[PDB]
Length: 132
DNA sequence: GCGAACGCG
DNA sequence: GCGAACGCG
Ligand SMILES: CCOCCOCCOCCO
Image 1 (cartoon, rainbow, N blue to C red):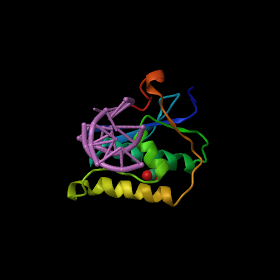
Image 2: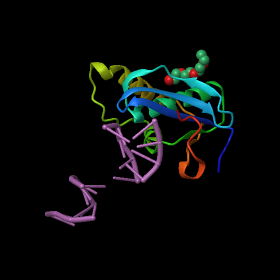
Image 3: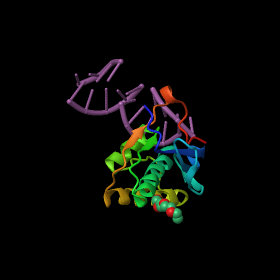
Image 4: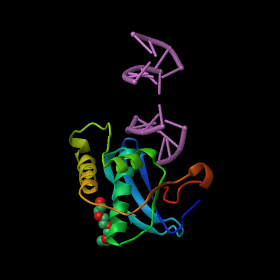
């Protein structure tokens, strides 16, 4: 069950696809540790993907040993694969999110990390803390 | 809508 | 064995 000294992340979208953001919070406190400026077009899974990787980079900067919780099978897998498999068309209106996703892929393939990435078990625990 | 997890040849 | 037909915001 829950490791409380941990960071939780979640994505939110106005439309899917649409404007997406994300945040990370302290799983115990609910303290908002970071939040990303709105991105004009993205998907839920892209947003999540950026969120996990932001967290990874947040924690590593700080030499944290805390784990990250995510409720996304997909984003978790993409992170473990160091490869994002989004179906989102690449055009003028999606270049920003795709630049962001590629760079985070790049980061994952050019760096190591200690952080355990753990499934937030929603049926048992409720809404992950980082939900909007 | 996003992406992962039965029937054919 | 291969390809078509859940959890979360
Ligand atoms: C300026 C406060 O430091 C925040 C550290 O987080 C850095 C995250 O880097 C961007 C990851 O995509």
